[PDB]
Amino acid sequence: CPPAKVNILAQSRPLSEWPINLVSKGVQEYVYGLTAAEREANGDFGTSRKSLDRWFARTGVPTHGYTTVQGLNLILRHTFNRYDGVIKKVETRNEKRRSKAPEETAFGPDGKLKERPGINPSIYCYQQVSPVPYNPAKHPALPFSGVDPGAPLPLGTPNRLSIPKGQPGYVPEWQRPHLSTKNKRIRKWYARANWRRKPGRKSVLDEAKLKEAALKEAIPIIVTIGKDWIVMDARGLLRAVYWRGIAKPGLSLKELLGFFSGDPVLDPKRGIATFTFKL
DNA sequence: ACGTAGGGGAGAATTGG
RNA sequence: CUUGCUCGGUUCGCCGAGACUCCCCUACGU
DNA sequence: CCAATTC
Image (tube, rainbow, N blue to C red; front, side, top):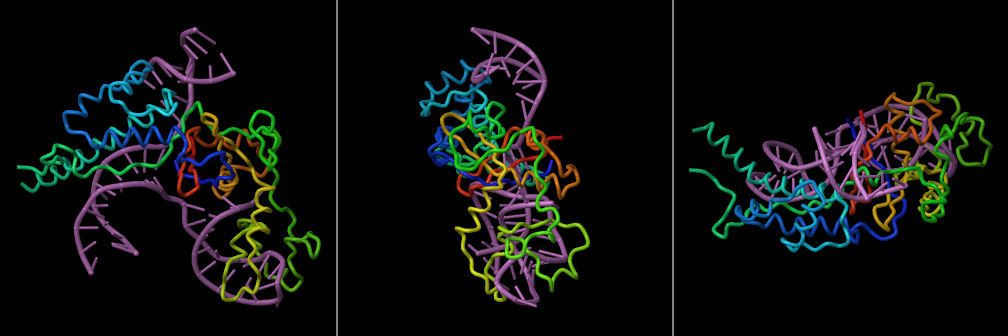
């Protein structure tokens, strides 16, 4: 199950103000700093509505309007597994000590866990919120158009030589001999690997011209949690199914992300979300 | 600032109002 | 083989050559 | 139609 990465196009509000992130951060901030007696007392979290509904009342963790069951089970199983990770580490670090031969516990005089886990900013998606083809009617308004999910996707730049002179993608005459006779990736005109600062490049970088060219031919997929929608560029998905030999040139969007899981993992600060290959 | 070293993590197929 | 990314040619129009198991967090060397 | 239940 190898990973594939996708760039983000637009979102209404940033991922910090998302209730799914705020609830996770609030839950994580409350749990890591708990004594070994508090984790067992407060570990009475189930996989049911009524179990989680009152768990916030007893523990007092803020709720920012997040009540979805599976979303809560993706930030409560994980938070207690990170908590157990430090104790298991010093217990597996106890295991190496045991092999060599009181102990090196993970609780100080205050009783708290001294090597407190850091807050994990990953926002884990679930089945009820999965990427779908961006339909202009159902989903909110965005400038970039959405493709039909049933029609096959276009093949990128066929017959590169047969491109008008003076129009983007033109291969000059002195350069047509000694071209790649073997198959490789076909980089686009607006590719940044052709336009970047190099001692030998006299060309001018203009980020406005290139980036606008990039999203007109984009492949948008959308994930909506509450009243927040994130829209992406499903071309890293397309390249992943191309350089790996699992796909052909003509392939529909509905079938493109069927290769991937319905649970993307987002990176709020880096601006990238990672897919995986469902097997 | 950097290897390292070592804990966490990366669905989906029914069922019920 | 439409994005992204590393290393090179270049007539600056784009070309050839690559990588693709990654993110988070706590620690310890230089 | 889509969260809660479930492994």
